[PDB]
Amino acid sequence: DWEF
Amino acid sequence: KSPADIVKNLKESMAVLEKSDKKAEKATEEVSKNLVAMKEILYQTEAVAQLAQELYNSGLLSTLVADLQLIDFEGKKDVAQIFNNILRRQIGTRTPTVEYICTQQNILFMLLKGYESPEIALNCGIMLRECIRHEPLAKIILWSEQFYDFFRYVEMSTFDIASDAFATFKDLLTRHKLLSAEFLEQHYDRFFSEYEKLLHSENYVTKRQSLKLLGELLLDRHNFTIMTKYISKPENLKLMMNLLRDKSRNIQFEAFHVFKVFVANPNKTQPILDILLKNQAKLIEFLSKFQNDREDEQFNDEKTYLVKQIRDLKRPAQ
Image 1 (cartoon, each protein chain N blue to C red):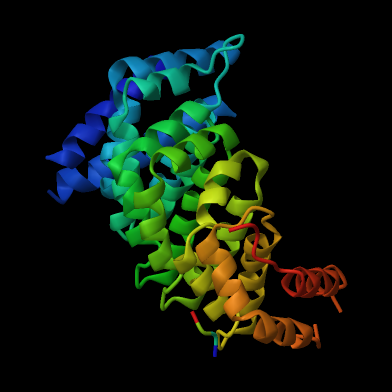
Image 2 (cartoon, rainbow over the protein chains, first blue to last red):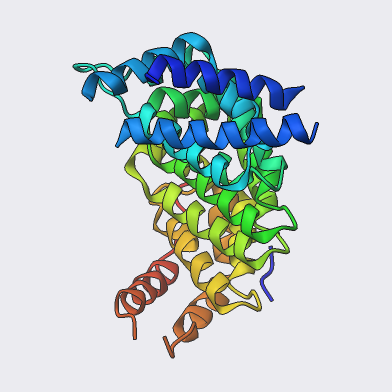
């Protein structure tokens, strides 16, 4: 998953 | 008889329909016959000229739109066909029907509201899209509050009508470039706030078409200021990155097209650069494997370019  | 007579008779029959059975059946038959007679005039150069003048003067053009719900199935299509022909009338450099509608704007508002009536929605769409070909009419519609009703129409449960409203909506946003660019700039916050919701539509079609249109809008040279602003917001990058992982392959692919725009930007805002750095290695790996099955070649070259762009990302001077 992306991390923002 | 002549154009004036046909216009007079049609105006009278329309009046009856607005007011049944015996009398209604006759008025419906008379409306149908007069509409067919008007078509025959369209297909005497002055007879046509005469019909147009009578149509403006009598208010019948406006009445035919206002009363469209009262007209029979084939008759509604004849109104559209007659309207579409008269709309293109030319006198030298002038388009009199366009000038006419500019001073009769309720015709456009009534046509737009028609999307809310199942039995006339498609005919309204047809006439609206013909109006939209003329920059002054596109402008009236685009600057109107009713333009925001398209966000509701394209999300309608009747998908065929939603799709038709989307074609009208897309035409408005893409046909007259300077006009659309000026609109988007002046109403940026409200427009993109509504558009952001389209990108979460349950109608897979509206969602895919909306993402595709966003890509087209951002890439047009006339929209440079709008694009620059859109690719500066963290929330927009976030949404596109999340769409790269959508369950739908087409959605991911359309999202990739917008994503590229964010990355190609030589002057990123810090919130944007920071998101890319925080996901640098992941993005490099992800892009190196993204739909590698797809032979597009332009697509493969774009992945190569983006992988290099991400690898080369650097914080500038503090």
